[PDB]
Image (tube, coloured by chain):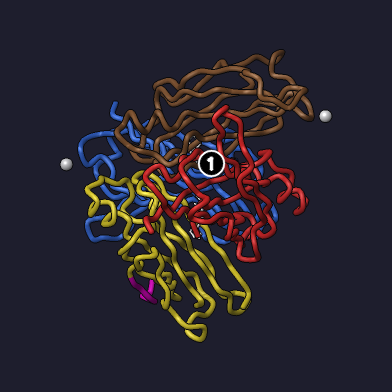
Chain colours: A yellow, B brown, C red, D blue
Amino acid sequence: CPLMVKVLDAVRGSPAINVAMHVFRKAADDTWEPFASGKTSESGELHGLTTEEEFVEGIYKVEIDTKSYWKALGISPFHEHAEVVFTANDSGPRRYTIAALLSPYSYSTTAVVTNP
Amino acid sequence: CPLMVKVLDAVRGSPAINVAMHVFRKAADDTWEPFASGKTSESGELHGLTTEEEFVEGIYKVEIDTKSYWKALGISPFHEHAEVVFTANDSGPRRYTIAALLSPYSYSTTAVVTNP
Amino acid sequence: CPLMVKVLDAVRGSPAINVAMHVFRKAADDTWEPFASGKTSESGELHGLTTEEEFVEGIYKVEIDTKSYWKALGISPFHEHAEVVFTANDSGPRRYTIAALLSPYSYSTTAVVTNP
Amino acid sequence: CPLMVKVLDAVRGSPAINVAMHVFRKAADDTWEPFASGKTSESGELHGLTTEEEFVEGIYKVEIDTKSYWKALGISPFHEHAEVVFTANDSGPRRYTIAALLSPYSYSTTAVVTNP
Ligand SMILES: Nc1c([N+](=O)[O-])ccc(Oc2ccccc2)c1Cl
Ligand SMILES: Nc1c([N+](=O)[O-])ccc(Oc2ccccc2)c1Cl
Ligand code: NA
Ligand code: NA
């Protein structure tokens, strides 16, 4: 599991389920190329985004559709989405967990990076 | 103003107004003695808790009554309070801003420490 | 697993390993009775603190020794410890995950509460 | 002052000083157009980015150059930048404070939205 995303809900004290996100990789012309995507499970986790061989050096952007999540709960949010932009695999493969904790007007994000 | 506390509401995107808090200082017998108390203003800030002369070296605890805050908004929150425990003025007088960002099931707290 | 604590390190991007903590339960005289304790594993997690039958209604305090964690890394921290105080099991058993994300001058904490 | 950004350093317990950031606004063709830029002061705050007349309805992005900040302190951070994307002034003019709390592998961001 080279890249996993975990999302939590700070209002309900629960995993954030069915949160959609796309992953992009920065292209040579500075545009964002589609790379992976999915929705969080009932555990708030999204596994299986990529494989070790496909996940090479680059700048990656995880764009998490937090706005649709809050609107489904009938809550008006601040952000259009939560974006996480980072260089990955510059020193060869690593395993990355991107975590996000969501509130309607705030989010926090952290990374856990491990050498396989 | 050597000690200031600022509290923000991550659900509503606003200062957390009229939040009560109590400050304690550890006594020689290791019990918590009352030190100061107050409530946040319309800006979410509590100023004037202490003075340079009174705010001596010690271990201090700020106990923020987050539970009453959420209950008054019709939210049943997770925590009884948000607690911040720290040694102050160990290397001479400093000015401390304690900030807290509140959600029903989560809080974040940070400190800004400056040398006058 | 009625009560689990997970701790992450925001400076190193890693689980916070070997973080010691004690759990207390508030007694009828408002004192804090010892309840459980342990240290986080290499995954940053502490499992096995209690059992469903022992973990009944009460106000619980998880006192996480963040200061010793940072001092072992040669980093001077702000807080004496990170405290998480919450009522548990007031509506019968639940499963609780307490998570904390640590920085030298800040911490964030959230809860995931699930009905078994 | 309809838009202000405040940045704090969770490692040092200080304002994050001399942090560069760029603000963009989504154009009719869905591209990001430059809107304003600046750097935080000794208080960690960036004031004067825009005016009430210029700060019309739209989708805005604040891109905070956290990577250069950490690198100058000798830290190799995780994120390329901290990004905040939001719709502004949808229901008439508001005043926005965007706050960010920075660690090498994590950031938290919140908004305070007030009606003048
Ligand atoms: N994370 C955080 C916390 N915190 O205690 O973690 C407190 C406040 C906060 O926003 C502000 C608000 C005012 C000044 C600086 C930062 C954030 Cl963004
Ligand atoms: N904010 C935060 C907190 N927290 O106690 O606030 C704890 C953990 C965390 O990342 C994770 C990491 C793994 C699983 C769930 C969340 C974040 Cl992002
Ligand atoms: Na001293
Ligand atoms: Na409108």
Q: Can residue B91 be seen in this view?
A: yes
Which residue is at the far bottom?
Answer: A53
> For the point 51% across and 86% down, which residue is it?
A53
Q: Which amino acid does label 1 sit on?
A: Tyr
Please state the horizontal and vertical placement of residue C102, each as a whole percent of the image. 60, 50
Rendered position, D10 above or below B63: below
Asked if residue C2 lies in the magenta stretch, the reply is no
Residue of label 1: C60
Rendered position, A80 above or below B47: below
> For the point 57% across and 39% down, which residue is it?
B110
Q: What span is in magenta?
A: A32-38
Dominant SS of magenta comes to strand
Please state the horizontal and vertical placement of residue C8, each as a whole percent of the image. 59, 56
Please state the horizontal and vertical placement of residue B63, each as a whole percent of the image. 55, 29
Quadrant for ligand 4 reads top left
**Which image quarter: residue B51?**
top right
